[PDB]
Amino acid sequence: QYNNENNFV
């Protein structure tokens, strides 16, 4: 299982 998040502000 691969779990990620990417937020760019």
Image (cartoon, helix red, strand yellow):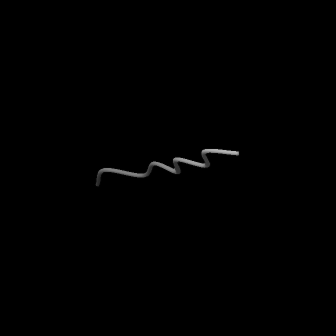
Q: In this orientation, which residue lies closer to the viewer: 5 or 8? A: 8
Q: How many marks?
A: 0
- In the picture provided, is 5 more to the left or to the right than 7? left
Image quarter where the N terminus lies is bottom left
Instruction: Please name the residue shown 45% across and 48% down the image.
Output: 4
Q: In this orientation, which residue lies closer to the viewer: 3 or 6? A: 6
Instruction: Please name the residue shown 61% across and 49% down the image.
Output: 7
Q: Residue furthest left?
A: 1
Give residue 3's position: percent from left, percent from top. 42, 52
Q: In this orientation, which residue lies closer to the viewer: 9 or 6? A: 9
Q: In this orientation, which residue lies closer to the viewer: 5 or 7? A: 7
Give residue 5's position: percent from left, percent from top. 53, 51
Give residue 6's position: percent from left, percent from top. 52, 47
- In the picture provided, is 3 more to the left or to the right than 9? left
Image quarter where the C terminus lies is top right
Q: Residue furthest right?
A: 9
